[PDB]
Image (cartoon, rainbow, N blue to C red; front, side, top):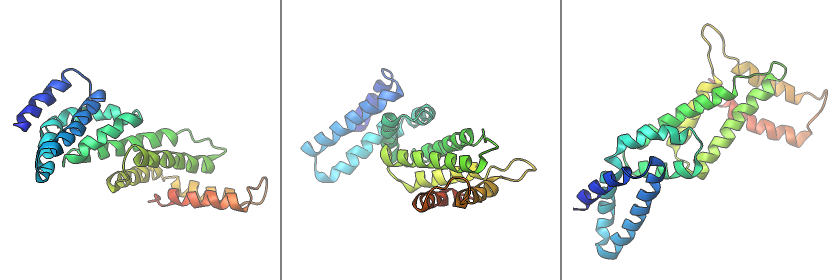
Amino acid sequence: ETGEYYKQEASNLLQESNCSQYMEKVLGRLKDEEIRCRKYLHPSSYTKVIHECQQRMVADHLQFLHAECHNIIRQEKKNDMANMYVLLRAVSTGLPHMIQELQNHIHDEGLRATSNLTQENMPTLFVESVLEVHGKFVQLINTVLNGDQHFMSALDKALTSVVNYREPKSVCKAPELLAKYCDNLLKKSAKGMTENEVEDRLTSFITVFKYID
């Protein structure tokens, strides 16, 4: 009976609100349902009512979630993709679509950064652009998401592809740019950057180095 009630309730909520605030209404229901599930039922039914709740409220409308999550992820919606993940976490086949789409988002975000390579500062700009993408997106997986290895591997697979950008019949410049970054930093000539600050940048340089194919 709670399956049929949330089969009707799930279809009723989407017809009134968009997918952005659909998450809040559904999370406003599961949070309330978990409260009343422990006020009435036996403790052994907590993991079966909620599973029946999400099956008829999330896994049922799985196509609606995957179709619109493209707009959610590719807008850096912090407060909206957080609720998007927790609903798809429970469904077995819901989560693998979100990581794949984010893996494409990092690929497109990285290529946008690594396209206007100024010829006078090629190595420092390329390493910093990859570090800025990695340094900001690791926060998203650690602030509005949980540091799941599925997402972290999605980031690593995406950053591996964008760093090792192989043009047709042409060699990738990733080994040359990263190597030149080290040489441009260990030079005592021109302006130095002290002992402590140089090794700090080189410590973060390893993150870019690990994605070299």
